[PDB]
Image 1 (cartoon, rainbow over the protein chains, first blue to last red):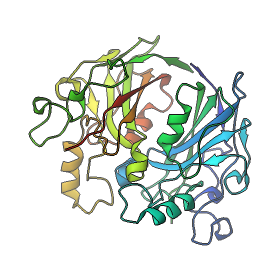
Image 2 (spheres, rainbow over the protein chains, first blue to last red; image 1 turned 120 degrees about the horizontal axis):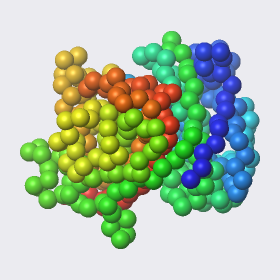
Image 3 (tube, rainbow over the protein chains, first blue to last red; image 1 turned 180 degrees about the vertical axis):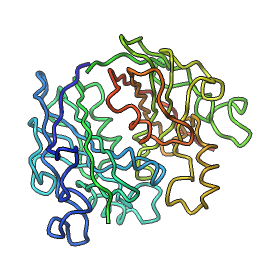
Image 4 (cartoon, one colour; image 1 turned 90 degrees about the vertical axis):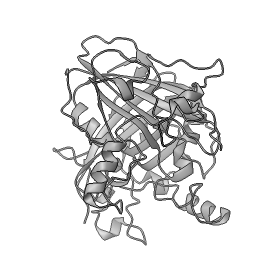
Amino acid sequence: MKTFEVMIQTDSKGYLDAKFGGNAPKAFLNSNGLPTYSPKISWQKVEGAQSYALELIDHDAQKVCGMPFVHWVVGNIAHNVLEENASMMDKRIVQGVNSLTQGFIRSPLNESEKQRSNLNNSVYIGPMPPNGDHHYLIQVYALDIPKLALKAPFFLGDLHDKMRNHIIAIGRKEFLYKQFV
Amino acid sequence: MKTFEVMIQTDSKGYLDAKFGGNAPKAFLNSNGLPTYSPKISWQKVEGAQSYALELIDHDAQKVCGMPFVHWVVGNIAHNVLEENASMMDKRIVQGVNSLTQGFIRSPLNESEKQRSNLNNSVYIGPMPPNGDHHYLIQVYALDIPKLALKAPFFLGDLHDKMRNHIIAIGRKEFLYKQFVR
């Protein structure tokens, strides 16, 4: 199993810009004040690959709420880049359900509202760390197949189910985002 | 940045034995019914590694409750192996808070109760998947320093803070565990 370099533009101190998370100027927040504007992320081409997948996870969220928080899951990435604002704009990628959802199985909403909430949250949600600055982990998977059989709404383990036995390489990369409010 | 192989004894079908997750015979549970009996996990020795660390996560939990679930967090592993029952028996390792904890910030519990909960749950908690069989992911880190500066209670994020810039290799292994019913 091989590895590859993953990149994302941060400042000198390794911080991603305010606009990509909770501290964003209002104009980069959606109707409800949520940072939905995804950053440009890119990585080395991996020979043999035919698509890539990506998960963005906050390990520092375990302290805050008991488990790590899922910010972004994306599969069917045809090329070695996600262009800035890809989450709202890219129409070829397929996107997984993030941890703001209230459509997980043990939720008290009915089947239809679970579905509505899952699709609603099948996007990038930006950093919003309450207890202080956090590191965030981008992990990129290089796959030996062009397409994953995934339809929104799908969850992190669904990505992994369809990726299983098809991963030729993995790339990791961390960034910082300042405390929120 | 290198990778290395990680091993765990499984079924011909890829399932870890019941005893490790609370379909377990009651002899392998604690007095409260919890699967705290950790499986033997080992991996190929890596060049330059002064210590190893491990984390065990269930991504399949995300669908169930909204987030992946942390089953086990461990640092200060001197050798390329954790022996069976290591979580209970190994004096040399340090262990992070698992996802049963109710000591996270923004739990309703008071400050002192949180500290207890965190410490009480600084152990391996085995698979208990409610909705069907789950895959679990073991991730092992090879480090270039012999000891991490970690003292229970500490979380997954803390493990990573101490390991940042010291990881010389990562190993990954998945296993299955049967749906848990009552």
